[PDB]
Length: 229
Length: 229
Image (cartoon, rainbow over all chains, first blue to last red; front, side, top):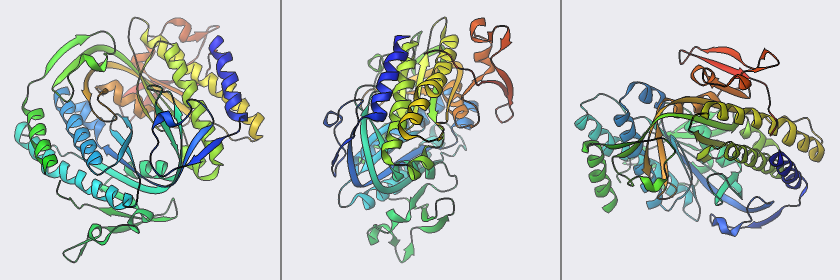
């Protein structure tokens, strides 16, 4: 069809066309980039956080839709409100998962504190409301994963003309970390090694445990800490 | 803080408030719903399609950034353009993954034809462009997964004030199908059983192979076929 011809032409132009790239520190506004063009912004260091609700199949399959809807809504609102409060830019949303990018001179400490605050919101705000209003033993499980790296971004048109796609290690690794079970927060060593001391130690106790990510050849750090919102 | 106080109050109201629900036959405008409220639309029958890349992490880690950006951009534009062309409504975007909802009397046939067209876009449009520009045998791997079920939706504020969360089997299962590797299109039995004959057979031969999804305890159907865009 005509769509096939249009896509063939544009796909060819995308593979053959020269790229135009500008370096920047902050997440761009979508209007800073040409839509569906070989135009990108290059962020030399940016910190990606994903916050993911776990156990969704279990929950959706067995629970009344009203309960599942309330879990999704409360987790996603708490997570997104806390991300915004810590200065993160929310860049994607899909189902169980929120993506944010942090920039600036405290991006790693901010992102990590954000993750620990999300754990507090789950354990200290949502969970007690769950046990009290529905009289259930259901436990809300979630993971926040964080990495930091160079990222490039281009403007695409999926939900609308203002979407951004992110190309770089942290966009992939932070997402992979949230796919792992058992710890509410996981960060790469590149994040941990930039944390202020108040984000690493409390009352003489380590807030993080090291865990080597054998597949990626880097260290990571996990935490069950909850930071009061 | 204002944040913790506001979250505690709103979370409590979200668990205690009764739901207001109206039935609808199409994907709602986000404005059809009250933001951050126990207000839902009930879609008695909907078909969910997810389309994603397979193996983007290793690609990003090993290929030139221009190559990865071209793969993401061309896959996502092809998939989203084909979804919209088949009358689907794009409901989520994150990284290498697109979600759409199809409604109406031909929703399953349209979604399945959409999936086979996406396979054609990959094999007949994008892959030859990879070969021509980059002169490489790197294979773009992708999966499209499809399920159909009742869904409820509510309006949330993640990227902006107009996000929708989708609650129901098809939103969960279609995403889970796309986490599996080895086949470009996977649909549940409930989708297969609604397909028009022209989407099931070609010259009297089956275009689909049955595969029991031992984890979910349901039958699925897979296809390696493609359909002209």
